[PDB]
Image (cartoon, coloured by chain):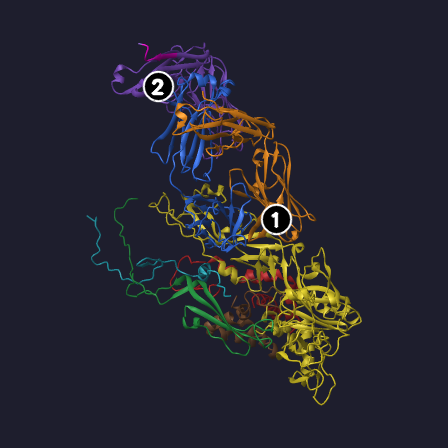
Chain colours: A orange, B yellow, C green, D cyan, E brown, F red, G blue, H purple
Amino acid sequence: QVQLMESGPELKKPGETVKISCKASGYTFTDYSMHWVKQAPGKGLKWMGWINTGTGEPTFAADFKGRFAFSLETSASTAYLQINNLKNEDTASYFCARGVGLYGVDYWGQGTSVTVSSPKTTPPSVYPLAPVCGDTTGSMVTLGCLVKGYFPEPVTVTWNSGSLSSGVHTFPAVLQSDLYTLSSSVTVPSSTWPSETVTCNVAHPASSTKVDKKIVPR
Amino acid sequence: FNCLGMGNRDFIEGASGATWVDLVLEGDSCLTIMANDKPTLDVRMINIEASQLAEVRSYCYHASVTDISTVARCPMTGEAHNEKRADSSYVCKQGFTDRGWGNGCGLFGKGSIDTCAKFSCTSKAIGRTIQPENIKYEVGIFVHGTTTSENHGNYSAQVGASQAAKFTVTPNAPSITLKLGDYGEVTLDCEPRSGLNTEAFYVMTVGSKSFLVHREWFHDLALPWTPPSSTAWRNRELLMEFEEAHATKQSVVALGSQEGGLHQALAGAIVVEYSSSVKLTSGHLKCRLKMDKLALKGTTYGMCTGKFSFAKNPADTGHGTVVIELSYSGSDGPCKIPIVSVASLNDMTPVGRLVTVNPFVATSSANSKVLVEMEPPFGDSYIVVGRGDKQINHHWHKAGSTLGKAFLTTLKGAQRLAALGDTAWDFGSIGGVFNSIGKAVHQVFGGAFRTLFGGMSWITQGLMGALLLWMGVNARDRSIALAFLATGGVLLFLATNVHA
Amino acid sequence: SQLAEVRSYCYHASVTDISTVARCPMTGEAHNEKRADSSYVCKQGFTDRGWGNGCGLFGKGSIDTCAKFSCTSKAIGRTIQPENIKYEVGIFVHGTTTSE
Amino acid sequence: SVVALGSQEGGLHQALAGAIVVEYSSSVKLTSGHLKCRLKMDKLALKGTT
Amino acid sequence: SVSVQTHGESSLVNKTETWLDSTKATRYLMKTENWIIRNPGYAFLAAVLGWMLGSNNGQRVVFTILLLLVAPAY
Amino acid sequence: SVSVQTHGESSLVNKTETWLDSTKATRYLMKTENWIIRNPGYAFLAAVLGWMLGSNNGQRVVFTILLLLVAPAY
Amino acid sequence: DIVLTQSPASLAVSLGQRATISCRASQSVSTSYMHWYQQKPGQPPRLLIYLVSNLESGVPSRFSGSGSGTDFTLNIHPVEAEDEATYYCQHIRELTRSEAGPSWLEIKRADAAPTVSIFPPSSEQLTSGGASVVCFLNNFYPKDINVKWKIDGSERQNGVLNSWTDQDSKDSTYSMSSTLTLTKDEYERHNSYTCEATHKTSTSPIVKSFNRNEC
Amino acid sequence: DIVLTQSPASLAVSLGQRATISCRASQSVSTSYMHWYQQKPGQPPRLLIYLVSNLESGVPSRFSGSGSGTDFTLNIHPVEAEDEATYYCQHIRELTRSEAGPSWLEIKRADAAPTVSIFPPSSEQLTSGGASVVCFLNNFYPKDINVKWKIDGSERQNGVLNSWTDQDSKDSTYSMSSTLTLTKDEYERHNSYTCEATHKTSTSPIVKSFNRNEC
């Protein structure tokens, strides 16, 4: 049961420093290499480098050389990716990888997405989105939840406390001024709206704001 | 883990006087240790495994010429200019186009050309190094107790039987102790610091496989090569060629795959297999067995009271002793197994000794098979099993009479002396005085001389000795043997050792 | 023009179909059906047998280890037909001439 | 197991030393000439003497 | 090159079968012979100079056979 | 083989740029030097042999420097 | 130093079909030492094949790694809804280790049009002075789509934010959100507000529009 | 490869004033062997200073080249209306031979606003199906100006074609034409066509417009 357990995803700001812990388990630690692979949030696996497990000697890819510290703690078998002078590029899911070496890397840190950026936690601005005549498709009147300008992700956007997942497409939260907008679309029959309450319920644990917005017609 | 039927199985002579012995063991060989109170012990390296390996540098053995660009200049324009020198990916070559008034220029016979070809590697190969902190040593240890043809061949069994163990030693943790259970506990004190020279070579990947190459010699490979990571190379032209200038025209052309040469370039190299790690085959290691807690069960059990039976028929090792396997009918188990090696039936005197010491029926289970070996002596002898005609015997012959074995003892020594160099003197285990200075004799000497004119292969240094021969006959008295010492042995010896 | 090839060479050949056909100690040299197809190539051999592995006698064995030969990449020569010998001779005589 | 040596093509090029570059498609065109031809200047004249 | 100046020999640890073994044994004699067998007219002139100079009999022979090796790999 | 035993030298007509030319000159000296550059320990002990024997001065060197080249690759 | 490319970038497939996923070693001959890695989104990738020819233990025999040294292929002869994943292949012969641009397994289905619904800024937003015209395009297959925001007949690509679901687990379609964010002044200095979307199911944009002057 | 850069790119000056035109040798020490080449528009160049230090014969001593080897200056202590021109500096020390990006002599004057006149496409042009809205921004000094074509309040940068005079021989102003070329269909589907001219003489664009609905 070899498992690479890393640190958790960590929100950071530029100019800072982050050290991602990776504890290795299920195997004699010294006997493999220990690799790091940057997976950029949208980009495929970009291999950060590796540190010697026995010697503790790091080596980095040309891009990863000089900003990054591969460090090990022998006894508890904890590999470390440390990123110094944090930069927005340092936001990504990072993976320690136990080397089977020339045979690649067998196993993987559960992932740590560092998030490096300035903003401060901000609540969502949530809009019950009332459809118009052009928004009624067949039986279904599509309804919407416009979540606006929150940091950080997530907001938990349900519909009538999640009783509607059915016509619900909650669309990915994306960046605005380092704040986030997800727009959730519940698709409900015109028989259920506005006859039944359809209320998008937006819970933002980071800003501790649970925002319930009921869509009523314009 | 065991010595059972192993290719190189060389038994181990307990001098007693200690429960400890410094040992030198190998991946291929299995060492079978017999001593007083100390049962027959199998000790073999499984393999030598260097765990984590680093790429020391890289080599491109097959290249592709790309984008041949020759910028030609007129006679007496001197140095030609083709800007691709600004790109290391290109290889640029100055030169000239011989001219008439007809071709490209207003003068005759001279010119200038700058021939730039973009270098591209078709195929590259990498050598790698070994940090001894990543070295393992997998040593299956075993002791001959109650065994079968299966358990004694199946480590998992002898795990439970506690007669065998496996493990790893490092320069970090050189020594380990291990218990045999009923037989007690033994200790191994190794020197993984001293086992190999991790830096005596590299691990050179040629094709899929990797290979051992002297890291001195490895850089000496003349071939387009690489920063261990990535890109900017050296002499990358050595796979590429040129042509005439016919007008401006000249082509750079790349040699085909030199991988075959790389293999050709590997003679002394050794097959090494990376898995998560390289597993080396040939063992060189110095460990110390310590038996102080190794003991003997079974002295109480009675002589087995019933018909024995061969579970397998009497068979010689090929290492000079005869192993059988006994399925024992009697249910009196656990019982001490009566068996001996005697000269004639009409004599009861045991002559040979037990390979497997203290043969022991493990349990009362009827017909339970027990695999045991003893040592027959020279000439004819008899495996004799049991007491009273319910006993059975069998004839055996071993023709190895001491004289020939005395050479097998002695002459192997020189083979054990040379090619193992200074480390050959741990065959002198529990040494001192004689054997201690014996190392020191060869120690400072072997570190010079044989290695100084070393690097010669087979007949090369052998013919040197063959060229050193006549200086023995042509010399002055008391000066004859002086120039004659290095002639025979240590030079022709290794040259006779490999014949062919 | 038309040149004839005496042979071909294989500078790059593939190992294919490795088949080892084994026998016991002293049971003698093994054979393989792969020796009946020259595309296959076999080699004999032996590996020591304890009672741990497969056989009664200690220290011998027999195996027929094979490989299908295939030529991955092959090299070729050609002989020149001495009648195909041609000599194409540009010949010139100097009269009025220009650079072009 | 059976293991094949690496492609010797580069070695073939190495096996070439004094080799002669020639281009054979349906025909070879050889570079270095050796021949013996007898010119005959009888019908060869001098134009322009007029 | 790729062909010449091999790792041969490792000669470390190694009681084992090397990567390329029987080659290095017969590389020396054969190709030296295979060249001088190819040029037998070369061979006999080497026996001349050994007797030409040094006039010492038993060490005169040292010149010849050692020279037969020379021209292979010059 | 593809290693040694090259067509070079053809030297039949063929007055031209050879396939490989300049590298052939450095075959013999360097790789034999490179080995005795690799083993100056040999170079220390090698050339002393000829001067030991024969007392014939100038020819005592004939063994020495020429046997130096004999050592690499036999 | 050595580069890889893994094709296709994604493949919409019937599960159980054989979709063989190519890979190639740009440099050298990687020989052995390429390895297939499935990453389902938001996971550490799961190593599939080792030496590019050999299954891991946890990966089923349906995965077939194949190809030699300049080229490699990841074959799943029974591609599956579980085989839906982001697949990687890695030359290891040389540090630096790198990966090929991955190959997704998509489960093929019928083409579905986007369910397109253009929501004007709610009074909650209109009271804020910001105005976002949000158009949810729901349950289209394929993912291949283009949204446009037309304003007074003049298309506005500004204030345009797009968020779309992935292959939608039940119908295996894709849903999208188109959003037209406006300053309520520019939102009220212009009138016609249109999300038109050309999706492979339609030869034309699928137009959902309102004018503030309408309702 | 040796670079020169000649600053400024242009200088608006009084004639008789001293406007010195700098130059510099990016490489080596060019030492001597830099020049000054006056080329007025539509002319073959005319060489002024040689060795960077020496007038040609025809060029009067008002021109003075100066500076040594990494840096250079073209001075005319009495710059003139005849000196209005484009000047170059040329390093000769090495092949290759090149020329620095010039300095221009502009004659400084009062700052004038563009007279801006937006003519809808001629009825002659409209009958052709093409529609070009021409906006003539006339007699402005300096040349610093910008055209902005606004359409139904939505500014259109497409079909815009700009043609402007140079420093205008009489008043030394500049005149500009802004031509908005529309399909008469989109010319007729939109109404207000507004060219607005921002100029250093005007803190705001000079707005000239027509709604086709107007006359």
Q: Where residue G78 sits: x, y (%)?
A: 44, 51
> Which three-letter amino acid code belongs to the residue tagged 2?
Leu
Magenta segment boundaries in residue numbering: H208-214
Residue linked to disc 2? H180
Indicate the secondary structure of the residue bearing disc 1: strand
Query: Considering only vertical position in the picture, is B454 above or below B372?
Result: above
Indicate the secondary structure of the residue bearing disc 2: strand
Residue at the (38%, 58%) spot, across then down: D21
Q: Where residue G193 sits: x, y (%)?
A: 41, 22
> Which three-letter amino acid code belongs to the residue tagged 1?
Gln
* Label of residue A3 in the image: 1
Is H18 or D19 nearer to us in this picture? D19
Q: Is residue E36 left or right of residue D39?
A: right
Q: Is residue H148 left or right of residue A48?
A: left
Q: Where residue B395 sits: x, y (%)?
A: 65, 85
* Label of residue H62 in the image: none
Is B447 or G40 nearer to us in this picture? G40
Could you say which quadrant of the image residue A67 lies in? Answer: top right
Task: Report how far apart the C-alphas of labels 1 and 2 lie in the structure.
Answer: 67 Å
Q: Chain of mark 2?
A: H
